[PDB]
């Protein structure tokens, strides 16, 4: 029985 | 979970004791049968897809294909949910419900078995009907880059369990966020437009029932002076007039002493035309029209509408 | 979880230990609603939505059913988190105070469960008021560029659940960043203006009730010299006047010897007219009215007062 | 977590074991408030917002309730961290310090719980003092373009926690770009002051307070060194003093003496005065980081929106 | 993570795996007399690194050692050479950090790597950090198209590079750049010595040619004064490239394009003992031109003469 | 990633999967006598690529082999074909890098791709890297209107191109680049390229040899005067002459009637068209029907730049 | 991306899920002799994409088939119709690129579209890419206000168009169309061999366009085609068809048909279809739709195509 978390990314644009 | 019609029983011991308890909590009303005042095509498709193959079951079979899906799109003010509630409280089918909450679990391996148990329950109980509300949050794009790995298995079990009695139905607000493979299984994507000058007059004549109204109000002027209103803002206008009837008097300065006599005098009074003027003077539409045109473009491009 | 009227108890044994702890942690210092200067229409809508169904529960039956939402939008400092505290004070209903740090949910599939338990618990205690503060966060557009897969689920749960009575306030500094459907469910959108030249005189003459004023009875002059003060700055003006009454007697050098009666000699000193000049020449308003003009434009183009 | 005054105990159970470690990592009598010269308004506000509610607490009630925030602003070398260390050293309050690096985590919903635990501990312990350095980040208007989502909820938690029990906190901040602050956050900061470059007379006192203790010649004219800088930033005067004190090592050529007789040459140099040639050759070498457009922008902002 | 002197041990429990590896990944025997010119930088590195180990009682109060230095000038002059020279001459720990050990796609790593780098540089020894090309890393803060995750790194450097009366362990921060006017107005206060390094004059290129040509057999026909008076406007790297083009030209005088395998190893045996005469330099002086016309040198000379503290 | 000589292996654990795949996606039968002209480019390639492979004991000290070259010229001459020829006639691994390999959506991926490219090019072999179109990749560093990622890619090249302080265990890397706009490079990246050389438009003898080379195998007559075809293309590029030969070779198809014959008498007549040779009138028509991509002002600008700041 | 011949399938696992959809969104009612005149374009299209299909063995070695063409000239002349005709006449896959598809939000998510487009065009059958309005994509590189987001798509076109050169997998023929060709690159113009000028006024061929367009079944005495073709100074190839549409819609409006109902409603539209066109509604079509072409574009295009044009 495993659990799952939530990360955060960082994307860029012009 | 209870038993079904015709004497059977379900054996759900393979899944855990909380998946049953979390999918059972979605399965005696007088909801509006005829009081939806537009969308004759949607009533035609629903009446030919749920009732006529269940009254004479040989009328739609095989080469005469009965339908299996519908993805209603449109502006956020028209009546998408009311038709689902009407066909829920009208017919004799076990109406299910699916949100974005009943398909999420903290553990791993429990976000995919819920959909399987749901479709197994729907194909076991009755000729059911599922109403997956706000499906644009459930099924997005599959092979993206900023997507967690938990949604791909949900959409995979969804598309693998889609083939199935069961008549699925869903309603969106943003239709272009749906998957490119998801629209193939939706056999009809019907656009729901805002009501025109002909429908608003019937809307006012139905929404002003039971309330004592003066015989001077002209429904054509009210139907023509609301260029831009959605479905809900007209009902908000009819609410605001009957509340302006209350606020015309003085009930804030006085309290306690014989107020029920003044409240009875308020219940005696009736709605004039100046109350409609004050109500229409101070009610704006919900949103400026761009999403209506964008959903009309999407249903003209990819939809069968 | 405590009980309610008629001794029933909630069966919240299908939720985790910290979810129920959060919803119980977000759940009567007597203010008065006539201790707020201005905003007559806000008090009118709050009256018709909270106080009158308690007195006469038979007038609100059909079309005259009470309101279900409200939004106060405007500049910062105009009294939006004060009417919520006043209506929390002088009512028998169960208050709530939801924010954005209350829905953190580091795991997956918990924020929508907290929102569902919050509404399912507010519909248990039968008169309830929910106050979502600063709904700019967790109330953005559903199809924005940078969004997660959980914020859209939170917004969808708000859209599903807002369709035994509750009443939901809100507060915003930037109302144009709200959604379309979530803007639609708020049946009352009300602009809050900066105080005029009449309300500022009332506000200073209400705020200065304890400290002895002697000869500065030119309250018309003192309310005509402040041009664009934003309501919560003229309280800082009076506070700067009282501390300037302190500042004229040099107390930086008096160390230990008789620091009880020397400050009792500052407890009998009156706020003369010399202090308000030295308080007006040292306090400036915090903003320019660009956000005020844009809020007025949005509430004139979309506001349902 | 320690136990506060009156022997109470904090029940931190719902927070994880690393949030509490971070807030514990955020948590003397070395300096005093007489070391800092100038800045009369900041000393007055600190005196009637930190010190005076400890001696006479039966006077600051009602309309005269003490202040609850402050933000300093000015040129980037004029001294606004030194005032925070001085009020940390001359007080009996559990002094916090918070930068913009210990509010960060790559998990969803850990940047806005550190702030909530921070304000709850600052209320729980004592009449505390929170000092947030470089607040131009975690500022910025919320209607900005290219703003990440969690950096909006950090500002929302800051906006909710900073208004509202006789438990006193005093949020203190410092920045160089004050016009890039949030709209609804520079309302909560009840006193926004300006701190200029030193005038013609404060630089002489700064020269004296730096060069006291070091043996110097009796013919150093302080008026000429005071009037000859004319635009120095306040830290560049201390840098000028350090250069004029190390020039007496750079005058005797100690670049080739190594091992033998060098260790006695430093003992011979340790008793040598700092003459006028050192200050002339240090004035020919040190120039300030000029471009006073930052000072003029800060002056115009703190004269159009500043509440001294 | 290794130990240090006096047998202590670091405890990195609050950091993940790939952060301490990214700081571990940035942790022969040439002398400081191989640098020609640059007396100011030699003097500052002397009284900031060398002297606080021999006599520690002198640098106590107002004579405390420095903490930073920015080298700024034209490209190809000896910025990255003095750093490796002072790395290989001293005994302290040397961190060669650059703008690619400070970036990751997650949020909250790029401002933790800097904190871990400064914590290790303070824990280990009187170490030295060498931030290369700081013009990339620290710009002006209130800028136009600045990303959000660069303000945190600039503020992290700005907060860590100045912070009690106890625990006086030393950290020296050396940095080099060639467009120095884009530095932040608050970051130039931290770097409290901003010396400028110029292009070599007529008396330094003679010594550079005489230093670079030792090790190969040459004739006594060449006049180094004429070669120092004709190579005008040359930087250091172009003078070394000229001195390399001469030896490859004396390779080029014997045509080996027709030979293939047969006695080719024995072909250069008559050439590996050949001298370098004046024809090679008289061809290489028109083979090689400088790299850039002087505009950046004039802009740096006008910058460092108004904001420079040498 | 496969192994190299002496059976070692690469530990690419600190990078993700898509970076390794994006670098692995960028990794015969020609010769160096197929390039008409360009003597000095062949000279630098000879004394920097194929001579240290045979006699490595000679190139030590001041005669260390070069590790840079940029071929900057007008856009008609041979600048990619020489790179493909030196890739074919060698034994070193080749890395072709354009400007759309070093691009990604996230933050901090282009620098890791450049770092992995240089680490694999040092690990695998005495390799060689061909960065085509360097002006879209290394531009200027202080111009108005550039993103905050191109400056970090430029700083990555500036740091990685020099280095290797350890004088022992020296593995060879050789960087080659082609450019049409040579006044659009940063000065600290222009300095890192030793041997910046110019590639000119072909002269009379080069055009004569190119027409003589490109017309083998195709049957021709014995009355073609190559001196007139050499002297009449005054101003042609090195790539327009093959276009002239191709138009003169399909003019023998345009001379007969295949546009009138529709279907029938078309494939039965193509069987005897393969033996018809090419006479002078086809070259006259092709010379009248082909004009060069003229405008020699850009050749003048590139030649003045390579004469002021060039190193050969 | 369904399939191709011989049952194989593409492996686009290295790209995103919106890039492949934006490329898949790119993939006729005329014959090849419907487009009259300009037979040089027909010559290049015959010896480029038509004839290598039947005989694959003749086009090898020096006589390799072409791989580029440019259709420059005045607007409204028949470039898109030629592209659609050569698409539908053969069995080639037909892509179509404009400037409105090579633009997205994320940095570097645009140059993957061109690489995926060319990889798909090589992966499928011998195909045709119709890059329309190339004056927007490829200008000059060293410009004054040149942005840094289109230089990479310029360089990607330059790299991808010419790329190892023998033993060809399948042919790929890229088209172009522009109204202004002097604002082009120098390394993108060179990849476009066989540049072709097409002229607007073909006066005697406009008579053939009249005879193929003016299909009016009544008015057997209204044959004034000589003056109607001699009054075609500056009339482009589309304004003639628009004039025929105006005349054929004004033959039913020169007679007063406004409010003719009540009695015999079905007869008023049936007695109108046989009305004979005259010169009076033809005068309305003559002085109504004026030609909007000036000699500042055509003379500059003839001055450009005479110097750098390889017919
Ligand atoms: N045709 C209609 N007949 C009766 N009422 C209608 C009609 N169209 C709209 N309404 C009114 O609009 C309101 C909202 O409609 P409904 O309850 O279906 O939710 P909805 O607007 O479909 O939800 P969403 O915001 O997701 O579109 C209802 O209160 C209803 O009174
Ligand atoms: N109209 C008013 N009547 C009485 N007091 C007021 C009024 N306006 C402002 N104040 C005073 O100003 C202070 C700030 O008011 P409040 O907390 O409502 O600001 P706010 O606008 O809700 O804050 P935010 O800008 O974060 O929404 C209150 O403490 C209140 O005492
Ligand atoms: N009024 C003053 N009296 C004495 N010393 C001062 C004064 N102002 C500045 N200093 C000097 O400033 C140095 C500390 O720098 P400072 O306090 O200016 O930080 P800061 O530059 O304000 O922080 P930031 O970089 O965030 O602006 C000390 O060495 C101190 O000698
Ligand atoms: N003063 C000097 N003495 C001896 N050699 C020098 C000197 N200056 C430069 N050189 C030579 O120049 C070459 C390049 O030096 P270096 O790498 O330091 O340039 P750089 O300043 O780092 O270039 P940039 O900083 O612009 O990238 C070195 O090989 C070195 O031998
Ligand atoms: N030579 C021609 N033969 C037959 N039809 C022609 C000819 N020239 C023009 N036309 C007609 O002109 C109409 C317009 O042509 P088309 O749609 O190609 O415009 P276009 O050239 O694409 O416009 P633009 O140049 O602005 O892109 C077509 O319907 C076509 O029938
Ligand atoms: Mg709904
Ligand atoms: Mg508020
Ligand atoms: Mg500071
Ligand atoms: Mg360098
Ligand atoms: Mg090329």
Image (cartoon, coloured by chain):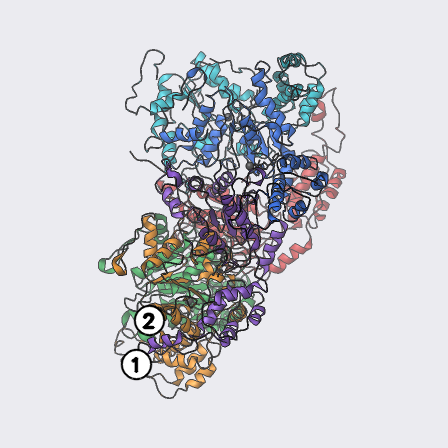
Chain colours: A brown, B cyan, C blue, D purple, E orange, F green, G red
Which residue sits at x=32%, y=81%? E216
The answer to whether mark 2 is within 8 Å of ligand 4 is: no
Which residue sits at x=60%, y=59%? G304
Are the numbered discs 1 and 2 placed on the same chain, yes or no? yes
Whole-percent x, y for residue G237 in the image? 64, 46
Q: Which chain does the residue under circle 2 lie in? A: E
G13 displayed left or right of C80 = left
Where's ligand 2: which quadrant? top right
What whole-number distance in Å separates the C-alpha atoms at marks 1 and 2? 51 Å
Secondary structure at numbered mark 1? loop
Q: Looking at the image, is C144 positioned above or below residue B233?
A: below
Q: Nearer the viewer, residue F206 or G281?
A: F206
Q: Nearer the viewer, residue G202 or B63?
A: B63
Specify whether residue D95 is in view.
yes
Residue extending furthest toward the bottom: E221
Which residue sits at x=57%, y=72%? D224
Specify whether residue F74 is in view.
no
- For disc 1, the marked residue is E271
In the rendered image, which quarter is residue B269 located in? top right
């Amino acid at each position: 029985e495993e659990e799952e978390e939530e990360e955060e990314e960082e994307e860029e644009e012009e | 979970l209870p038993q079904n019609s015709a004497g059977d029983s379900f054996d759900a011991s393979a899944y855990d004791a909380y998946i049953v308890q979390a999918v059972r909590g979605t399965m005696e009303n007088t909801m509006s049968l005829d009081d939806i005042i537009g969308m004759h095509d949607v009533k035609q498709v629903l009446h030919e897809a749920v009732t006529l193959p269940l009254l004479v079951p040989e009328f739609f079979q095989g080469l005469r294909s009965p339908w299996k899906a519908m993805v209603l799109a449109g502006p956020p003010g028209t009546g998408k949910t009311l038709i689902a509630r009407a066909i829920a409280s009208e017919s004799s089918s076990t109406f299910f419900t699916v949100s974005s909450t009943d398909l999420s679990s903290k553990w791993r391996g429990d976000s995919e078995k819920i959909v399987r148990l749901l479709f197994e329950l729907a194909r076991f109980y009755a000729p059911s009907i599922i109403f997956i509300d706000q499906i644009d949050t459930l099924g997005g794009q599959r092979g993206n880059s900023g997507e967690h790995e938990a949604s791909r298995r949900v959409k995979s079990e969804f598309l693998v369990q889609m083939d199935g009695r069961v008549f699925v139905l869903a309603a969106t607000n943003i239709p272009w966020e749906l998957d490119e493979a998801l629209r193939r299984r939706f056999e009809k994507r019907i656009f729901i437009p805002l009501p025109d000058i002909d429908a608003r007059k019937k809307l006012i004549e139905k929404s002003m029932e039971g309330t004592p109204k003066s015989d001077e109000i002209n429904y054509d002027d009210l139907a023509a002076r609301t260029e831009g209103f959605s479905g809900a803002d007209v009902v908000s206008l009819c609410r605001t007039a009957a509340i302006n009837v209350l606020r015309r008097y003085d009930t804030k300065s006085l309290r306690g002493g014989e107020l029920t006599a003044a409240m009875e005098s308020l219940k005696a009074e009736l709605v004039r035309n100046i109350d409609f003027e004050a109500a229409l003077q101070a009610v704006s539409p919900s949103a400026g029209p761009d999403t209506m045109l964008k959903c009309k473009e999407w249903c003209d491009s990819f939809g069968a509408m």
